[PDB]
Length: 50
Length: 50
Image (cartoon, rainbow over all chains, first blue to last red; front, top):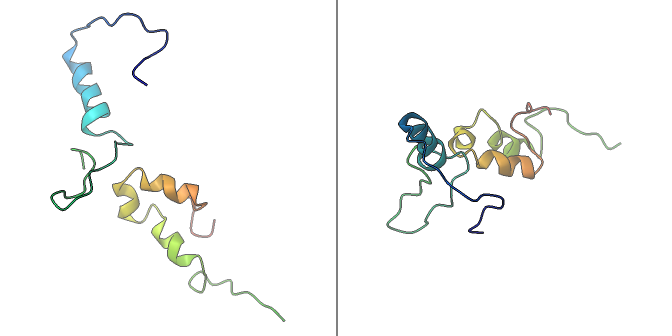
């Protein structure tokens, strides 16, 4: 679960524009986000985009 | 003689199909809710008749 097969080194490309774009696509507004927390203190949204 | 209504409104499946349509913003809301409609054999990409 923690691994990626055939991947050995991560190298930085220091490219902010792509970084932003990816953070946007992957974390801030994924199409299929991780499940919401359901509880009294929570409004029910799944992502920041929403 | 057993006869079947062809009117969309007099259709046992109309309620669910109304919920599962690209028309409904609850489907736009969660890109994930579009999957459940497809899984339960009611694709919102298709028209009401389909």
